[PDB]
Amino acid sequence: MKLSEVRKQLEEARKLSPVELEKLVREKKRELMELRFQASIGQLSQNHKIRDLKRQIARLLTVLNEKRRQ
RNA sequence: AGAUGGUAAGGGCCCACGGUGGAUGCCUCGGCACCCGAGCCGAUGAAGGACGUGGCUACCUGCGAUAAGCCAGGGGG
Ligand SMILES: [Mg+2]
Ligand SMILES: [Mg+2]
Ligand SMILES: [Mg+2]
Ligand SMILES: [Mg+2]
Ligand SMILES: [Mg+2]
Ligand SMILES: [Mg+2]
Ligand SMILES: [Mg+2]
Ligand SMILES: [Mg+2]
Ligand SMILES: [Mg+2]
Ligand SMILES: [Mg+2]
Ligand SMILES: [Mg+2]
Ligand SMILES: [Mg+2]
C-alpha cells in the first residue's frame, strides 16, 4: 500500500470506535478470504493485495488495541 | 660342415602426453590466546523448544493467527 494511504488509514482508523474497528476488521478478514480463494484458483495476478490486506488488518487491530489499552 | 641375424604372446628400463588422486603454495567467511569492556534472566511465564507463518517456499533466518511482520520516537538518504 502507498505510504500516504497508510497514514490515511491510521488517521481514519484512529477516529473510529472499538466497535467500528471490530466491524471493519471483520470485513477485511472477509475480503482476505475472498482473495485467498482467488489466489488458489489462479485468478489473482495482483498478489501484492494479500500482503496489504493482512497488514491493514494488523494496523487496525493494533489501533483497536490502542483504544482499549487505557 | 660351420657360423651369424630379423620373431615379441607378453614383459622390463627410459621419454612424451594424458587419466585418477588431492599433496603443496597462495588465499580466508572461521578459529585461538591475551587484554579491556560488560555481566544476570524468570509467574508481566524465562532458558530452551514444538507447530505454524511467503501469491508460488524444501531448508536457514525473521516473526507469532496482527505471524520475513503492527504502532511510535530517534538515526540515515
Ligand atoms: Mg634368431
Ligand atoms: Mg617387445
Ligand atoms: Mg601385443
Ligand atoms: Mg627384466
Ligand atoms: Mg597427469
Ligand atoms: Mg604466507
Ligand atoms: Mg551475560
Ligand atoms: Mg523462547
Ligand atoms: Mg521457522
Ligand atoms: Mg508499515
Ligand atoms: Mg521508524
Ligand atoms: Mg523515521
Image: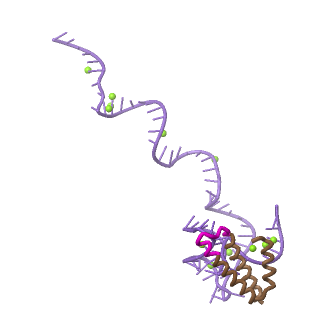
User: With respect to residue A70, does A31 lie above or below?
Assistant: above
Instruction: Left or right? Give the position of B54 relative to B72.
Output: left
Q: Position of residue B55 (x, y in %)?
A: 62, 70
Residue at 66% over, 81% down:
A30
Classify A20 as above or below B14: below
Chain seen in purple: B
Quadrant position of residue B4: top left
Residue B1 at x, y percent in the picture: 16, 11
Quadrant in the picture for residue A42 = bottom right
* Of residues A45 and B3, the one drawn nearer to the viewer in this rendering: A45
x then y, percent, for residue B64: 65, 79
Relative depth, front residue between B39 and A31? A31
Figure quadrant of the N terminus of chain A: bottom right
Q: Position of residue B15 (x, y in %)?
A: 46, 30
Q: Where is the C terminus of chain A found, in terms of image quarters?
A: bottom right
Which quarter is ligand 2 in?
top left
Magenta span of residues: A35-47
Q: Nearer the viewer, residue A14 or B50?
A: A14
Where is A51 relative to A26, above or below? Answer: above
**For residue A9: magenta?**
no
Total marks in image: 0
- Could you tell me which residue is drawn at 72 percent across and 87 percent down? A23
Q: What residue lies at 76% left-to-right and 85% top-to-bottom?
A: A66
Task: Determine the colour of chain A.
Answer: brown
Judge left or right: residue B23 versus residue A18. Answer: left
